[PDB]
Image (cartoon, rainbow, N blue to C red):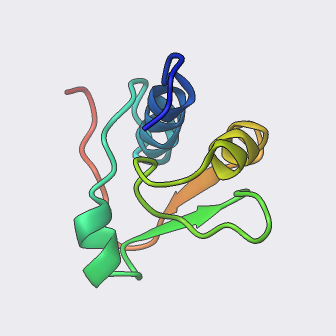
């Protein structure tokens, strides 16, 4: 319930998605199966995120977190714990 232009949200979206891709060893951004990771916390590892900020759907965070995350976009790093992905899609 605010006025302006919700961009960060999307920015963060592509961010987490971007990380996933790189983590998957791909060269393209891929959505993050938070639903899975949720039930399976030993599926993908998420790090680099800002302190005092967990790792969940970017569609909930606040201007701060949204920014913090973005402020740690270069720090944010994903590591495939248990999943393994194919090559050349």
Q: Is residue 68 above or below residue 22?
A: below
Most extreme residue toward the left is: 89
72 lies left or right of 1: right
Q: Residue at x 68, y 46 (%)?
A: 69
Residue 42 point in image, percent of width and height: 40, 82
Q: Residue at x 53, y 65 (%)?
A: 55
The answer to which of 10 and 23 lies nearer the viewer is 10
Indicate the quadrant containing the C terminus: top left, top right, bottom left or bottom right: top left
Q: Is residue 41 above or below residue 25?
A: below
34 lies left or right of 7: left
| Count of numbered circles on the image | 0
The answer to which of 24 and 6 lies nearer the viewer is 6
Q: Residue at x 71, y 39 (%)?
A: 67
Q: Residue at x 60, y 50 (%)?
A: 62
Indicate the quadrant containing the N terminus: top left, top right, bottom left or bottom right: top left
Residue 44 point in image, percent of width and height: 43, 67
Name the quadrant containing residue 14.
top left
Name the quadrant containing residue 34.
bottom left
Q: Is residue 40 above or below residue 77?
A: below
Residue 35 point in image, percent of width and height: 24, 67
């Amino acid at each position: 319930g605010s006025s302006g232009s919700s961009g960060l949200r999307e920015q963060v979206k592509e961010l987490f998605n971007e990380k996933y891709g790189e983590a998957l060893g791909l060269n393209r951004p891929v959505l993050v199966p938070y639903k899975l990771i949720r039930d399976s916390p030993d599926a993908v590892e998420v790090t680099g995120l800002p302190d005092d900020i967990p790792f969940r759907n970017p569609n909930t965070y606040d201007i701060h977190r949204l920014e913090k995350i973005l402020k740690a976009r270069e720090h944010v790093r994903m590591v495939i714990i248990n999943q393994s992905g194919p090559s050349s899609g």
